[PDB]
Image (spheres, coloured by chain):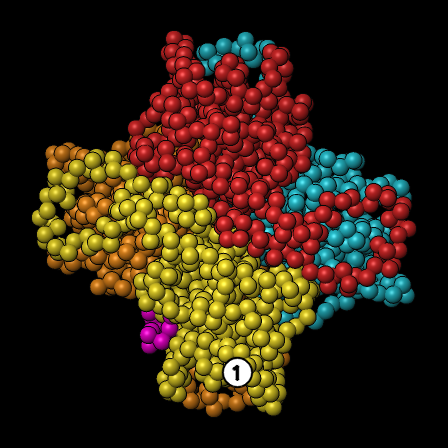
Chain colours: A cyan, B red, C orange, D yellow
Amino acid sequence: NYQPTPEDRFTFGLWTVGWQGRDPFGDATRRALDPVESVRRLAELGAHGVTFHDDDLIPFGSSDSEREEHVKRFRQALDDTGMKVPMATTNLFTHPVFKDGGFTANDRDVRRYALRKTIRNIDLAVELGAETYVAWGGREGAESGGAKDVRDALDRMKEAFDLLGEYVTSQGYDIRFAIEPKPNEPRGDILLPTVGHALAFIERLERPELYGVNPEVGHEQMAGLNFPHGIAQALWAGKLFHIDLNGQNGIKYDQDLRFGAGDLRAAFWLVDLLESAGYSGPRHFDFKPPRTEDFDGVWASAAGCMRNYLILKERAAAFRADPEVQEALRASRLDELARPTAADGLQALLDDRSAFEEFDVDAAAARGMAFERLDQLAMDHLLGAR
Amino acid sequence: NYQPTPEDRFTFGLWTVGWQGRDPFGDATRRALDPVESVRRLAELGAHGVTFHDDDLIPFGSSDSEREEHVKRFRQALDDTGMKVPMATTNLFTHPVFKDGGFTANDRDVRRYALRKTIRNIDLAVELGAETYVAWGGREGAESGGAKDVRDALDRMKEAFDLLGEYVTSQGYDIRFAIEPKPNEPRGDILLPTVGHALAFIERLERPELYGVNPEVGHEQMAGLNFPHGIAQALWAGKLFHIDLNGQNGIKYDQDLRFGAGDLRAAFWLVDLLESAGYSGPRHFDFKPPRTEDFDGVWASAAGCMRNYLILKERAAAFRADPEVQEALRASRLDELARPTAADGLQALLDDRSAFEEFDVDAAAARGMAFERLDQLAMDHLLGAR
Amino acid sequence: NYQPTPEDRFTFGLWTVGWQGRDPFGDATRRALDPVESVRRLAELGAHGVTFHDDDLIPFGSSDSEREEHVKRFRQALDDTGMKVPMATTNLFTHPVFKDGGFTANDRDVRRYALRKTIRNIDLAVELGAETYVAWGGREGAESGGAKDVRDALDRMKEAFDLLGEYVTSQGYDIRFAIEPKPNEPRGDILLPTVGHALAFIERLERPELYGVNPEVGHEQMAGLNFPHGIAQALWAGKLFHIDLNGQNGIKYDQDLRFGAGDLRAAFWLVDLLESAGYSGPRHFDFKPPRTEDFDGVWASAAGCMRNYLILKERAAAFRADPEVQEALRASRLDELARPTAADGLQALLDDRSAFEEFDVDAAAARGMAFERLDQLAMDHLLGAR
Amino acid sequence: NYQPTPEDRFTFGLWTVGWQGRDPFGDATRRALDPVESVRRLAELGAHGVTFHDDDLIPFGSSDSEREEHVKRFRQALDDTGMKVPMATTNLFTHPVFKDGGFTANDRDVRRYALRKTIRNIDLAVELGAETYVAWGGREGAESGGAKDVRDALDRMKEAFDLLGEYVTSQGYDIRFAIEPKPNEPRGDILLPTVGHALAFIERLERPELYGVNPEVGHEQMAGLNFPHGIAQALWAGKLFHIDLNGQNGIKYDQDLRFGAGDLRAAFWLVDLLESAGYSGPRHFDFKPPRTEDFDGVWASAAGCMRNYLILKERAAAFRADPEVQEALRASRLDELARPTAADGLQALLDDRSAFEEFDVDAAAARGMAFERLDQLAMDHLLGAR
Ligand SMILES: [Co+2]
Ligand SMILES: [Co+2]
Ligand SMILES: [Co+2]
Ligand SMILES: [Co+2]
Ligand SMILES: [Co+2]
Ligand SMILES: [Co+2]
Ligand SMILES: [Co+2]
Ligand SMILES: [Co+2]
């Protein structure tokens, strides 16, 4: 069962299934894929759409006539399959010119180039129908303390994002930006290393409403953080504009395993949260089929991303709908967590002897939270052991 | 040399030098210290002041007459020594009533109690002259996914901080709040786990100007993050209201080693940043003399916190003042990082062929950043090997 | 379903369900349990037996008559319930005398005391029928580099274990030792930090056959290691004498969550390995019911340890027995991994042109490993989604 | 000062200074270096020698005549400069044929090829004068649990190392092997992930005396382990055959920073240990000049490796020779740690009432260890602040 269809809004980057398998220590294990072929194969699996960096769709340094032909062929594949392009992004990390950054490169000429490269691809993104434009500043950061003054770098990063906001406003485009945090890799430390840092930065932009976050499962887990909690804070802020789904085993290099691999229970709680909250954006996979795999394994790994999401969706929904779980949630006071602490106001709280002078602290301390029974019901639902 | 004096603004929590050595696996190794004795010993070492949780100064459950006598004795010790009290905080973590949180406990009665307990100690803090009131929500969080809906918890945390802001405004107090992030420990995951998450949260409070952060070296390092970078983002935001200095060896339990221990180069870059930026708040140590130590070792460890700060301050200042370093900084384009990317404006950037059509990407890529020579000058200055 | 019975050989430490909830930052949340009550409650749940540190069964400093009465009551509870005592251990970590270690304390008198304390409890262990005597040297290590010369400490640790081996041989006891590694906590770094380090150390003891390892899920995961892989190396070495089962979320303080919590897929692969290998020792839980819980939650958490093991056992067995999985294992060459590389011998390998001169490296490189399809069959079996 | 000369025995891999800067997310930033040029430049800096993988010296797939000419040119550069070749190794990780391993590949034909490739280069290593032959099994491991049975893989790894030992014995070569552990990267988990695991494995080889370890600073730190402690255990075992020096910031991708970068205090304690122990092998750097650098920065980074070792050597020697430190070491009972616990024997210990019945546990517990004063003397010596 668990068959995806385009209604499920699953999307994939061209660079995911198209990854040829080069790693720090290894040459490619697979031939390059034509984007047309990836669009056709992903549609066959039941994907809704694809995403791209500029340089995945149009080789870097292409002439205008080559650019036009690459876009024409890609548009034909989209039209042949019904696939969409909900998101696009810029490659500001592969070319050696970006070795110290794009928007926060120490060289000013590089910063200006990075902005022009981005702007060119925003126009293309809009042409192809994208609603979201991601920015992963993977080269923004440092290996050493003197190399990068972070206050100056944040000034440059704000100028860049503000210019991009002025550009989209000037053109009357509806597209919005999603900043993707990552704590490290390829830089020793990356600027805006977590969802929190990116959310905080956005509040200092001139038009914050144009910007949200694009969190990635594995990135927050590279800092040992709880990905569902970070997603909850992004949702609380109204800033979950896009999301990248994959798997990661804790604090390592970025593994980009298929979704559901890595921390399975975190995957369960993530799906539970997205579905509970009614997140309506793409469920995008930013993953890499391991380099051990041939093309059959690439498509199996892609299919597994979607299958795992659908299994988890079923189990999370069954958990929340189970009367026994609903009673356990009330036994654990989840209902009381959702009630205001002091809707009666400050002065009433100050005058309330039940809140201090007559609060029986020992009686309250003795009341168990019943969280372990609740969590074992969650385990039983995930495992199909009810 | 490197002798601290009160002008250096070094402060210590009562709970630091007063830690009796109990850990997850171990009983106390030292007798309790009277706060009067810690104030006298810290003053002898050249400290400027001390800080307290409510329950470090006044045992939990004290009568009004006991409270008054504890405060009277402490005030006498302050007056005898010239020590100040720049910061105070609430213990919302030790008593079993707070096992699921204070401000975000699932039990509403506990949330209301936590607020009353905090308010009582804000009044005391102001009496004692404190400018900053720290809040470390160490119990806010979860060990399991169903136990805590994070959006609801953030709603409760905002209500609590907003009520506290209304309280201080109503009283005409000048005190400001500093929220202390930590990623985990004692909860499996703590809410507001990093500086970024706390900065982002503050922007959603009703009176954000009343709130900043109190980052701790070891807390950000428990997420593998770069503490100087996070401090730079807090400074960029205008939110470094207080800071906690200590040492930590990476991703472990919170070690609370003396400042300078743990990541020494991060300590160097931190001091460089605080001094460069002209941070004018207390240099507060939140550390624990290891439980291996007797009282002589407690005071040696405290003295070492201050000594290490002063050594690092000298070395960072020598680095920045060295003409050879100044030339290396220009060779690495730190000066260009500090210049606006496009003060000429968006349309000029769009019309600038030097930024795209005529940008020689290969020439720019070939220019080395010279960061390793710069970093070895920094190493040589730190080690006194110039 | 998934009901444990004593035949399943599930065991629990007295200190697990008996943990009162004290943590670095918190007082006890539960009253102390009488060991008699824990034996009765665990038997009711279907446990096979219990384990103890000396000081969990007999309070430290007890008189001979108090000792005798504590043991008499415990033996009655064992006899009333049919519970066994397969393992015992020494507390060489709680009392302040052990603040720098037991066997590797810098103070020689402490080292000698630690040995006498251990020997006294080996005699008790044997009286109670234990086959395995665990040693977790949680205080062996350092917070600073000068405090502990590790070569000298390893000399002292070998002398201690050798003396213990001489003691058991002298008495004609059948009991064997199991050394429990942990990388850190409560010491900044603990000696013998992983399964590998402990296995290597054992090979240098005078009677290595008397010693094996007692790995704990969460301990190896505190170093980011793969617990099933480490168990496989222990099994390969013939040294898995005992095992501690629990849950952990990666690189943090030691969480001691119930088994199945933390890394669920690692729990699956662990059970698969133990069952495949025919491990016949106790399935022992070294866990802590979270301090949020009352006693009902303690017993629910304990029951969940056993339930999760039994669910995982069923799913792992179904995976290995599924003809589709068996075919996927052959497609991924797991059968070839189990065949000798060169049973033909060195000279034949050297003369084999198919191994070098005529090896078609490109054809071999092109053959996919089919690991993603295999892993998604494993996921489907774990989740009950076949 | 701190000028290295060949007497210092500093060595570098060709792949270190020759790294062109390709990373997971980035193309090369530097042109390829001819090994002849690296030998000349390293000699100019005061290096003693160089090391190589087969494929760094002779491009993969070279003809016999190309092989001979590459070796001839390299030998001329060695002879021109006086540089040595103390160590060599095999590249069993870059070519796609090794995507599942060399010695533990699931495909048997690949395992046999990996052995022939290694044997060919052992002969070359011996020709060039190498004493040590390193093996880093970077592809040995898995991303998923079903893909690799670790007991079977360890059987294959033992067969491979045993065959290599039979080969060197058959040829009468004096060369010995050094196994290099790493916990992860490029595989999700690597087999023999730490020094301990490798030491334990070696004890099960047929001729253990032929094998030791080649630990790398950053590899053990990728597991959060204490590198000096692991080196001490290797020295204790008599197995430190070679060492790789670099820098790493904790639990991340393998950074390969220059030695002294990353954890500076760990670098200090490492040098202290190597020098104290009289380690006489090469001080080999396995590092990567950051891709931000041009060739001038490559040579500056290489020079900094050696400079930092020499600074640390001076400071560690001054620490150990300082009478004040010597007295602090006795105050902390480091002398007592080095004395046998019970040279009087088991029966005397059992009969010694001072070890149990008459041991004043409270008096011993009250004696402070004085470790913080000792560690601040170590800090002061490292920083040149005495
Ligand atoms: Co990623
Ligand atoms: Co991504
Ligand atoms: Co802390
Ligand atoms: Co703090
Ligand atoms: Co544990
Ligand atoms: Co244990
Ligand atoms: Co490395
Ligand atoms: Co290496």
Q: Give the extent of the magenta segment.
A: D203-212
Give the number of callouts. Answer: 1
Residue at (81, 61) in percent of width and height: B360
Around disc 1, counting alpha carbons within 10 Å, would you say few (fewer than 14), some (14 to 19), or many (20 or more)? few
In front here: D63 or C60? D63
In front here: A136 or C144? C144
Residue at (37, 86) in percent of width and height: D172
Picture coordinates of residue A21, whole percent (x, y): 64, 66
Question: Is B62 colored magenta in this rendering?
Answer: no
Q: Is residue C386 above or below residue C102?
A: below
The answer to which quarter of the image holds residue C279 is bottom left
In front here: B130 or A134? B130
- Host chain of mark 1: D
- Residue underneath mark 1: D79
Picture coordinates of residue D154, whole percent (x, y): 41, 69
Report the side of B31 relative to B73 (left or right): left
Picture coordinates of residue A49, whole percent (x, y): 76, 54
Instruction: Please state which amino acid type lies under the numbered disc 1.
Output: Asp
Report the side of C212 relative to B42 (left or right): left
Kindly tell me whether residue A276 is visible in this rendering: no
Report the side of D67 relative to C168 (left or right): right
